Image (cartoon, rainbow, N blue to C red):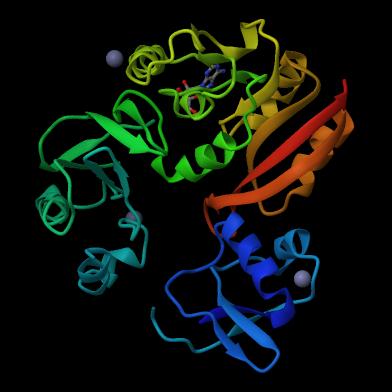
Length: 320
Ligand SMILES: Nc1ncnc2c1ncn2[C@@H]1O[C@H](CO)[C@@H](O)[C@H]1O
Ligand SMILES: [Zn+2]
Ligand SMILES: [Zn+2]
Ligand SMILES: [Zn+2]
């Protein structure tokens, strides 16, 4: 339906970038027509694409052929799916399925979606909406164990923030951490980024939510990383740690913390910054003015609202 048309010579070069930005759509066969490649792509503003593509391109409606619960629901529910109330996107944390439904629906029909989600989906439990949750189908437990990138994480979805669709981010980070690195995880959560950074020789895992620190400790124990990860409960603001790599996993408010992170990091070090926006500019100015910094990599993590993304930038602070 929506394809990126490009001269096939930049075929692979480009194909990779779309992936790195979780843009490529895998539900369609990249077809070739003459000197061109049509890569099915998720919807995106023509503008932001310019910032991650150096070649010329076009966004077009192109017919293409195809290469699970999401189905049956969609068809048999367009009524509510086409007006908030219900979303065709759920998360899976451990063995726990978590739906996105609105209060505006009679439980007797709302619970039914769960009872019929505990069916077309491999789980032990089912809830819907860190906010408050409602038990719909399966077991009534909120504490589970997540598996991702080889490690395991203890998560109690009802007491601490955690995003399974962000594992890709931990994978990428996993490949960047050197043996000599000292990481300061400003917003650690149950500790997904801290464990993904094992190669580092020291890790400062900070988080103001006590439950995030209770489970984080259990995770540090579970992945055998006691002499590596130093857990710290507190407002990151009032912490005095130093390090050459700073991870800011708080997209919604990252910006209101940049000054602290710059005060923690060393010169020559990188700030893994996650934010929100339609472009990258506002997030770059912000740093570009605060420091003598340098972008080392910039990706689009995922979609937030409409054309509202969760960007990720990698900043090298060359001089405070
Ligand atoms: N100022 C803060 N200091 C430490 N952790 C924080 C802060 N703000 C949010 N968090 C943590 O970020 C995690 C979600 O990314 C949550 O565990 C939340 O408690
Ligand atoms: Zn090229
Ligand atoms: Zn309404
Ligand atoms: Zn607890």
